[PDB]
Amino acid sequence: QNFRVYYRDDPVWKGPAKLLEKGEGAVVIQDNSDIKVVPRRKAKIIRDYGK
Amino acid sequence: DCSPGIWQLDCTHLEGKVILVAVHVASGYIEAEVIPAETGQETAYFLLKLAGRWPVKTVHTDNGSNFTSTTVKAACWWAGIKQEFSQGVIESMNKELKKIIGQVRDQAEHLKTAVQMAVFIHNKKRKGGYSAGERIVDIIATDI
Amino acid sequence: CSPGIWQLDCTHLEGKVILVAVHVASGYIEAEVIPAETGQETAYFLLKLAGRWPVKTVHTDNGSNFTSTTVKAACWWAGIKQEFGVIESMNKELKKIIGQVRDQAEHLKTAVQMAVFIHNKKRKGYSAGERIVDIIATDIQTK
Amino acid sequence: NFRVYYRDDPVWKGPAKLLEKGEGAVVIQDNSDIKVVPRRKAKIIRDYGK
Ligand SMILES: Cc1ccc(C2CC2)c(-c2cc(F)c3c(c2C)CCCO3)c1[C@H](OC1CC1)C(=O)O
Ligand SMILES: Cc1ccc(C2CC2)c(-c2cc(F)c3c(c2C)CCCO3)c1[C@H](OC1CC1)C(=O)O
Ligand SMILES: [Cl-]
Ligand SMILES: [Mg+2]
Ligand SMILES: [Mg+2]
């Protein structure tokens, strides 16, 4: 059970990024070595459902 | 971690339209769709459908921008598919598919109809002596 | 015989038309969001289905897309016999899963294929995807 | 072996028996009637998957 985050800053989707924390309004992620705070609506948190 | 789960995907083109083709390398079985644009979104959607049908473990593609896109990464992550970027199989299959399409093209108005007739023809043809469509089902069931 | 028997039906979500095929003996499903509930779209779906599985008999209700000449043409070319509550149960199950995953995707069609994947891979002890492959391979291997 | 579907009315009619396929028109028989239909209004389909 692990997660990667795909997100938009630019309508192009970025990712995968590491999920650092999830809140009711935002997700904190690390893409490469930059930490970013991303509104929930602009992020998809996707698990490796199919293994 | 062997041949039952390994697929190759590539795009070919006819009549200005984009055809996305998947081949199960060990059987020669194929699936194809005419997609409206050669984008990550259309490729990811194709892959989710494919992964729901078969136990897709590895997909081998070239470096076309739709295959290296973020949207396809997301699809493979969710579905559990490893991407890798026996040799030249899909390129040979593209040619064979276009050959069959040309043989039946005048039997349908729409290119997509002839594409799917061609897929059917290829998958059902017994080489002896099983067909590609029989070979994939036999390979996967034995791997269960 | 059970290897070749399928049921097809349309269901509706978000004003979109979902065409569902169920392999009766396994519970395996495939589905597509089609732009209109027409014979042309139904026939194209059947041609794709018949190219991947040994489709011998298809059971449907009497919806006009299923009784259309275009679908009769598909079934004649592909060698399919047409007959006129497995699929209905399956429509409800598919919609339940779709509802559970709907906010994970922008597009309804994405959620539909996620739900198909979820349904087909779930081990209830084999999954529907394992069962269809096993049923059909047994028929092939025993001639 | 072959079926011809054809239009006159947007619904596809047939199947009819194929008698001759020309490049401009098709001669068919549908319920005792001999009909000549333009190629563009005809679909000639074989029971490939029998
Ligand atoms: C439009 C869009 C844009 C960006 C993405 C990805 C990078 C974030 C996706 C997408 C693609 C997936 F394959 C996928 C998922 C998503 C969310 C979720 C898990 C199952 O696999 C989609 C997706 O549509 C695409 C035709 C599939 C949608 O409907 O949201
Ligand atoms: C547009 C149209 C109109 C009428 C028909 C039928 C009554 C004559 C067909 C049709 C349907 C088939 F299922 C089919 C074939 C044809 C020709 C050829 C052999 C394999 O199966 C089509 C067909 O498109 C439909 C989405 C498939 C096309 O592209 O020509
Ligand atoms: Cl927050
Ligand atoms: Mg290529
Ligand atoms: Mg119905």
Image (cartoon, coloured by chain):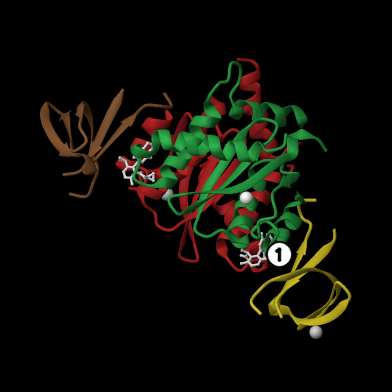
Chain colours: A yellow, B green, C red, D brown
In this view of the protein, can residue B102 be seen by the observer? yes
For image coordinates 64% across by 52% down, the residue present is B48
**Residue D13 occupies quadrant:** top left
Count every numbered label the image shows and give the total.
Answer: 1
Q: Which residue is at the front of the view, C98 or B23?
A: B23
Q: Which residue is at the front of the view, B24 or A21?
A: B24
For image coordinates 23% across by 35% down, the residue present is D14
Apparent side of residue C39 relative to residue B42 in the rendered image (left or right):
left
The CB of the residue at mark 1 lies under 8 Å from ligand 1 = yes
**Residue D12 occupies quadrant:** top left
The residue type indicated by label 1 comes to: Thr
Give percent across and percent down for residue B31: 57, 41
If the image is split into quadrants, where does the C terminus of chain D sit? top left
Give percent across and percent down for residue B88: 68, 38
Apparent side of residue C36 relative to residue B43 in the rendered image (left or right):
left
If the image is split into quadrants, where does the N terminus of chain D sit? top left
Neighbor class of circle 1 (other Cα within 10 Å; few <14, some 14-19, many 20+) is many
Give percent across and percent down for residue B43: 61, 56
Vertical placement of residue A13 versus C95, above or below = below
SS for callout 1 = helix
| Residue at mark 1 | B70
User: Given the image, what chain letter belongs to the residue carrying mark 1?
Assistant: B
For image coordinates 22% across by 36% down, the residue present is D23
**Residue B58 occupies quadrant:** top right
